[PDB]
Amino acid sequence: YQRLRHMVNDKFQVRSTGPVNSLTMQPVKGRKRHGGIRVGEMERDALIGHGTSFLLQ
Amino acid sequence: SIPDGFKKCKHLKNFPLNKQQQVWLIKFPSNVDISKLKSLPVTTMTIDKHDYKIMDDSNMTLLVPSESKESLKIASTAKDNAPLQFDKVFSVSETAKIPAIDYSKVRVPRKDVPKVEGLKLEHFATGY
Amino acid sequence: MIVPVRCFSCGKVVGDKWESYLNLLQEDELDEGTALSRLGLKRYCCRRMILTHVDLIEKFLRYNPLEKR
Amino acid sequence: SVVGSLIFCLDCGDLLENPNAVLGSNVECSQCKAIYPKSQFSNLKVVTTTADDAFPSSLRAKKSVVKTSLKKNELKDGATIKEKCPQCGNEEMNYHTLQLRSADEGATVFYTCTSCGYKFRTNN
Amino acid sequence: LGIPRLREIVMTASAAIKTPQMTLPIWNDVSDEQADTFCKSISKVLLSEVIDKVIVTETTGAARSYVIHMRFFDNNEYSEEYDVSKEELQNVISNQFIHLLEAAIVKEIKKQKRANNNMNKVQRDRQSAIISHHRFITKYNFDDESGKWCEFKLELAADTEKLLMVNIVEEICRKSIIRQIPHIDRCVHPEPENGKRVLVTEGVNFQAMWDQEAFIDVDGITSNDVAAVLKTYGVEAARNTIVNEINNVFSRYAISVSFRHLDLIADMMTRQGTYLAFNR
Amino acid sequence: LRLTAEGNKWRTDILKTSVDTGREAAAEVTNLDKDTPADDPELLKRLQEILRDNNKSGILDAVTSSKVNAITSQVVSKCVPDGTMKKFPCNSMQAMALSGAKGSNVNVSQIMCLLGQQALEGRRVPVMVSGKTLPSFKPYETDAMAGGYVKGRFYSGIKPQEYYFHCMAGREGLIDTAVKTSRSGYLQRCLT
Amino acid sequence: SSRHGQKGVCSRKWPTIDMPFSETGIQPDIIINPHAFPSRMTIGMFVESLAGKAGAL
Amino acid sequence: GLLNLGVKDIGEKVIFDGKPGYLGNKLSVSVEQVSIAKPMSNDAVERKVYPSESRQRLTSYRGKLLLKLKWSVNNGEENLFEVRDCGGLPVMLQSNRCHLNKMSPYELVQHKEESDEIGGYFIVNGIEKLIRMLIVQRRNHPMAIIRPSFANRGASYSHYGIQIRSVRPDQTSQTNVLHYLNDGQVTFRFSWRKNEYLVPVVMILKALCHTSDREIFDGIIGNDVKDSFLTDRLELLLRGFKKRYPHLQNRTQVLQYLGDKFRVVFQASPDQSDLEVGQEVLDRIVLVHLGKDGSQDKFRMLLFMIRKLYSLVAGECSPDNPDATQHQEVLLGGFLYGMILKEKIDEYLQNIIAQVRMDINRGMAINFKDKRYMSRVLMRVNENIGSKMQYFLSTGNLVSQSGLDLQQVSGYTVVAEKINFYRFISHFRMVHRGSFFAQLKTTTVRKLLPESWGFLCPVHTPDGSPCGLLNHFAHKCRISTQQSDVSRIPSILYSLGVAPASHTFAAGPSLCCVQIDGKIIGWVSHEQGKIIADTLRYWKVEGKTPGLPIDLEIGYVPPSTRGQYPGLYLFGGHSRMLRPVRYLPLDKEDIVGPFEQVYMNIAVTPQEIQNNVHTHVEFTPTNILSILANLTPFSDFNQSPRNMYQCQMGKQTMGTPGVALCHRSDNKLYRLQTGQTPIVKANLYDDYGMDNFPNGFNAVVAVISYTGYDMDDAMIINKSADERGFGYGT
Amino acid sequence: SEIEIESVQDQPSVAVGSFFKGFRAPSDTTFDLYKKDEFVLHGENERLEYEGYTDSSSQASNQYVVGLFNPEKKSIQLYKAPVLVSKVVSKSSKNLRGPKIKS
RNA sequence: AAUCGAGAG
DNA sequence: ATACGCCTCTCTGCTTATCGGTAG
DNA sequence: CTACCGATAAGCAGATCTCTCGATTGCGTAT
Ligand SMILES: [Zn+2]
Ligand SMILES: [Zn+2]
Ligand SMILES: [Zn+2]
């Protein structure tokens, strides 16, 4: 048995509040800089299709 | 522009061409002693304990010297202002003998993976 | 790198048997199985821990920062 | 001299001009400056047929001696398995597997009946 | 199939479908053999598909004559294979192919400046007509009795340098068409699907199949193309063929999509009376 | 994953029928006489024409594939489940192939009975310009194994040639999934 | 992972007493689901486990 | 050496001042010798510097590059020499420019490196780098090509064409593409600078050597004088040339026309006559692999290429697949270094000439003999050739003024990561087709073909984007790095029956064409050609005849209906791919290449050696696989995608990088604490010494559905084993 | 059967020329034979030059022979006559050039 | 911040 | 040393040139 | 007859899921 190098301490990230982007006042990119994750186009489309509108907002 | 180191042949030997004699063009490799060339087949001759192939094979012209022994005139005997094409041409080439495969020795049936020896009961119930 | 103190599966202390295994292999012309049986390793879980140890620490040790070479 | 539709000079080998493009009764070698009469060159003929792969036709396919056409009836796709048909229940139901969506995702099989023609592409 | 087809239907709404096809129901009394005869009579046949070989015999000795002797397949072969007659073939040769050939020859020249003839006087009038109507022809004779060959001399002038006169003939022979319904290149009679007899032709031209009422149920003529259906059948038929097409892709992959979804997609696409698409 | 002695006997007896399927398929695709020898010069000439022409190559690779797949189906039906030494419900491999928990009868047949013909796109394995499908096979080989018919099974391992053909097929699968990942969608974005 | 492309993340560290024990007293250090094999078809892992047990014996 | 051959063939670039038909004074600068040394430090008297120091200082490991110019004036009146250092040239470890060149394992361990260190990589800025091995078209072989882009190039262009890659002894590459035009004319294409050029093929034929037109007719058309296709095509070509260029009635006029046409791009000297500059372009472009003073050979080669193109367009020969290993070879990585060094020194000469020309155009205090002037002008250009090379290593960007025949600019050097020794050894065996093919949509280039049996590993290939592109080498596949001594093979072939080329007057695929390194030797029948190939292989295997090295590649191509173009082709050059095989007669090891393999029967094991079908056999089937693809146990029982994923994930484990980790400063290093040797392993596990770098641990694995926490892919680890150090790493 | 050899003539007696296909020459052409077994030939006329030479690469291995074979006997008159390649130049436009450099 | 390389799903 | 000035292989549509058909 | 149009042929503009790491980012003149 071989132990691969993709340990889980390099994968998890959590953000409640923190640093924000310069001109958009939105969360920064990157796990190591304390940034938020992206709710993209497909996430937006799926959040509309639920009829979940307060959730999407 | 005469090349350096090249000497013109001021005299040349003759060329006795007049069933009349045919003219043949024959090739030899450097590995043939043309000096003591005892004979040639028409075919797998042996020369100096070595075998050669002989077979048959016109662009190439014949340059026979004229009655001056200072240059060459183009050969012609039928009076057609055309070179007298060789009546027969032969070629000599090296040959080698390739060993036949000994299938009796090279067709080896597959040997099964050899069973280990000295194998005994290495596992016994607890308390034994 | 160096011999593990205990067998991974059961926990039988195999850390005190590497030198003895080497001696039984070198001095006597014992097979690995015979040497391990004479070493007191019966379960193949314990047998593998000494049969397959590589001992890379000896190679590691030849690079000593604190001794002139 | 003249070969088929071409004439070459006998003395230097340069390509002579086509006779019917120059003056009468004499043509000139450009290199040797020699003279060649426009006689002895009565015709410059070249007979050429087609590529024999030029015209791909159904008759050209049937012109051959090998088998060229595969009928729909004569093709038995094979790969018979004993899966259960969800439409009728005939035992035969052809198959084919095509890994999808990853180098690790599960396989899917294109189950196809032979009686009712029903299709079923079910992963599991 | 698949994403390319869905791009055509939904993302492009191309009028020029990559592979247009027509579905032509047959009357239940027309036999299968008669259906294949109808297929042969409808399908396009080029002049190339009936010529075995063409022998071009140039002779520059000051007119550069260019005798051409095009060999045909045996009549009993090619008539039975393509429903083509000797007279129709002769008309095609005498009318279309020679004019095309001479057009190609003059284009090449313009770029380049930078078995027996025992006539029956009918062939002689034909040859005189061809000679008059054509810019280079000087000889012409057709195997009227056997329909196996055709030879004609295309005489030229020594001003012009060498021509291939074989690649030219090959290209023109591929170009020229013996008979053709516009936009149709082939009518193939597949095996029935769901017990209904159908002919499928490789191009969509609705107004041309309406002639053969005796063979085709024109009430059932539906085709692959949506733009053509929208042109000749209106918006609603276009919506129906949109739904059937976008359902045919998923069925062949055995993927079930509720017809409500496809219906909503089709109604959004044809909401302006036209064949819109999901693009900018 | 094992069979019985008589199960393996059935398997080997049916596979011994696959010594002539490829040759007969070739002999009929070249419109030749049946029972024609595999070294016939006329057969080799017609096979060379088939190799040169892509459409005729497709015809050969369809007919031969049909016959060898028939042989494979015979083997699978005859040797499963009547050949396994351990049977359902005891046989866990067969159990989870039957129950749909994981796997399929195709996988079970591949492990226990036959790997069968490998098909690259719709045709068999590629043929080199010399008429050789592999260095090991002579030019214009009318053998099923030469054309990619893997008669081995994952229980008893596959020969080097069949291993190479199987690698061709696996690489084809990974290339297909590479194409799918590269060009996947934007249809959904344009619709939505 | 094993040497047969049988990767998989460590789900839980099972306690030794909760692990199944054999008649010889050994508890495996790795538990692999039997359902990994029918689709992957890595019979090499089966024959390797066989040979590794025999060699360790 | 390659560098000295390159500086030789570079030539001299001259400048004038015009100072009193006196064109001015002549200054022809050139470099005639380039020397390198193992790196030293001034820490007075130089002390040897070992790569451990470079690694530990997070700096580079580069020596001294010595350049001696030749400041020659007016055809050798006075010669000035100056040995100028040009910055630090990085060198690869375990090479003769490294201090570890022959150190035993004991010495290597003493000097802090490793027990069984392998070099092959560079150290730049404290980061290890390596030069990947690109795979390119086979050198010096004209292969018929059918390509749609050829016709897309313009009107009257067709798909057909012949492309040849010729290589100089410097190992630089020149492409000569023979397009075909539907009217009848053939257009020789080449590319000197980044721009391309088109030349009628008869013009270049006549610029080569004094020839008639009947000789061209006979050299392109053999005794096949009844083939109307050929006669008409060649008549169109000859008459078109005789029309468009009627005044060019001799070789000198043709050459002067070429020299007139090519003046500014070739940077021709104002001294050089048009005739001699035309000869310069002819010898610097056309079939460079024959070199200068080989005009008759180039003429025969071009006639061969033209007749082959007409054979292709008549459908009498099949196209040659450009992405099959049968027609390929690999750029070694040191040869890329040599070519880029030649380019950099060429730019260096151009820079010093630009400086002296700036001195001309700003002032006049200039004198070629003035050594003060020479020192002042040399010390005002940028002589950081070595720093340019370090940039090339550390970026992978090929900053070239011209660009070699490489179709890509970037992606040449990649880091050699030390996660794991499987990864490290895998860097040195991977072949990339190129980034051009990385960004493409044609799947067929990504296939696996029966032409890579034993050369490319069928298994070792990453999935994802680089699938089928980045494919590794079979562990017994060797790449030749030396030219075989072919000086005597022409002498042997003539004895065998290869009738000499110069006076045979034959051509066409109806006879065999015997060629060596892209240089026609003679012409012979097909039966006799097969016999000659057999005899060559036999005499090469029994190493008695001193004319036939073992690396000789006897590619015989029999007459096949619409197949590959026939002929007997011999090779001996660099960059070939070679692999051992057992020649059945005499039962001894033979060496075969991808070109010749696809026409010979090589039994996979001795049990199925058929009668009169086989002449070779593998030593073992296992040598067709890579090291990673051979270390997988019982891999013939697995499904192939699973083997491929193992090849990928063996390079991703946390094993041991090495043992000298106390003397390295790598950015990130994963190390396994306690490894073990496998109980069940391949034989080649020991041969490659993998036990020095254990990768995994033996574990007791239960195939059991017991937990419920491992269903899809997860697995359960015993907690007690984890507390006992099972699978621990730092 | 086999054919006997009378006498191999190592001294230059005959030469062989290969100009091109279908070559014919005037009755007043003669060629200058030089030796160094390599030869360099030269023949001139009013409008042409028969500039030729041997190929040293081919000659060092292969050697040709011209022989007269008696029908009424079993003997061959062998001779050592090498073959020279010949490029026929023309006096008409051999020395026709252009200006050295265009301004 | 752009690219380049390496990878995870 | 240091501040000014600068450099080879896709695929839909929408929009325009160009040398001739086309009703009154 | 004459605008007046127009079926070609030709030119031109835009796309082609999320995530984590590292390495590197340019050069000629003139006071
Ligand atoms: Zn234990
Ligand atoms: Zn002449
Ligand atoms: Zn059914």
Image (cartoon, coloured by chain):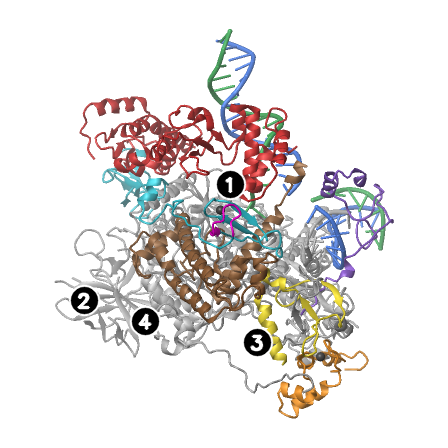
Chain colours: A purple, C orange, D cyan, E red, F brown, G yellow, K green, L blue
State how far apart marks 3 and 1 are (Cα): 54 Å
Query: Magenta segment range?
Result: D84-93
Query: Which chain does the residue under circle 3 lie in?
Result: H
The one of E105 and H81 positioned closer to us in this rendering: E105
Looking at the image, residue B77 sits to the left or right of residue H475; the answer is left
- Magenta stretch holds residue I76: no
- Give the prevailing secondary structure in the magenta stretch: loop
Residue D15 in view, yes or no = no
- Reading the image, the residue beneath label 2 is I69
The one of B81 and D62 positioned closer to us in this rendering: D62
State how far apart marks 1 and 2 are (Cα): 62 Å
State whether label 2 is within 8 Å of ligand 2: no
Three-letter amino acid code at disc 4? Answer: Thr
Looking at the figure, which quarter contains the C terminus of chain E?
Answer: top right
Rendered location of residue E81, percent (x, y): 32, 36
Viewer-nearest of labels 3 and 4? 3
Query: Which chain does the residue under circle 2 lie in?
Result: I
State how far apart marks 3 and 4 are (Cα): 44 Å
State how far apart marks 2 and 3 are (Cα): 69 Å
State how far apart marks 1 and 4 are (Cα): 51 Å
Crowd tier of the residue under label 1, counting other residues whose Cα lies within 10 Å: few below 14, some 14–19, many 20 or above: few
In the picture, the disc for residue H152 is 1
Three-letter amino acid code at disc 2? Answer: Phe
- Reading the image, the residue beneath label 3 is H683
- Reading the image, the residue beneath label 4 is B95
